[PDB]
Amino acid sequence: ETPSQKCEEKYKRKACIHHCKYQYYGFIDVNYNIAQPEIRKFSNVLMDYGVVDRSKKRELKKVMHDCAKKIKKEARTGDHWLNCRTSIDYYRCVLTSKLIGPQRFDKAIQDYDKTISV
């Protein structure tokens, strides 16, 4: 029904659960890519839920940009492209930034998740 409900059911490759949710949220593409629209969706959701103030947009989108740039570069290093692991690695990198409040981030994603089918 709700993404997490549906992803957890699906994987019951457990790591893939994370990518699963993120594609439903629209934070990651269905081919594992992160591009402008993904970055738009992610940054917007964070702001609309107040996790980050809108006076920070350029710089929030900046970390997501450089994180994307960085995951791809590490993926090419290992001679492969984006995958379940890179989807997890993208969140990690994004959560290392001081802009985001971990508890606040988590609850936002949990709230935003409740607003989706299926």
Image (cartoon, grey):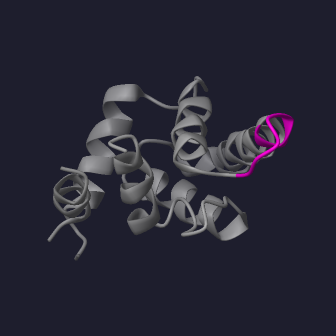
Residue 96 rendering spot, x and y as whole percentages: 58, 24
Residue drawn at (21%, 52%) of the image: 8
- Relative placement, left or right, of 68 versus 107 is right
State the quadrant of the C terminus. Answer: bottom left
Residue 59 rendering spot, x and y as whole percentages: 72, 42
**Placement of 93 over or under 42, stated as above or below:** above
For this rendering, which residue is in front, 118 or 43? 118
**Residue 77 shown left or right of residue 50 in the figure:** right
How many marks can you see? 0
Asked if residue 82 is positioned above or below residue 25 in the image, the reply reads above
Residue 28 lies, with reference to residue 53, above or below; the image says below
In the rendered structure, does residue 78 fall within the stretch colored magenta? yes
Q: Where is residue 80 shown, x and y percent of the image?
A: 76, 47
Left or right? Give the position of 42 relative to 15: right
Residue 103 appears in view: yes
Q: What residue is rendered at 56% in x and 55% in y?
A: 43
Q: Nearer the viewer, residue 81 or 105?
A: 81
Indicate the position of residue 69 as horizontal and vertical percent values.
80, 45
Position of the N terminus, as image quadrant, is: bottom left
Q: Is residue 29 above or below residue 8?
A: below
Residue placed at 73% from the left, 51% from the top?
81
- Does residue 50 appear in the picture of this structure? no
Q: Residue furthest bottom?
A: 117
In the displayed structure, does residue 74 sit left or right of residue 92?
right
Q: Report which quarter residue 10 is drawn in.
A: bottom left
Residue 57 in the magenta stretch? The answer is no
Magenta-tinted stretch: 75-81
